[PDB]
Length: 18
Image (cartoon, rainbow, N blue to C red):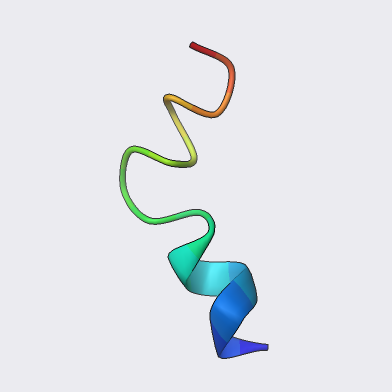
């Protein structure tokens, strides 16, 4: 659960594609 957030921290979610 919480891990799903850190994995998408402001940047991991954007840099997600970049």
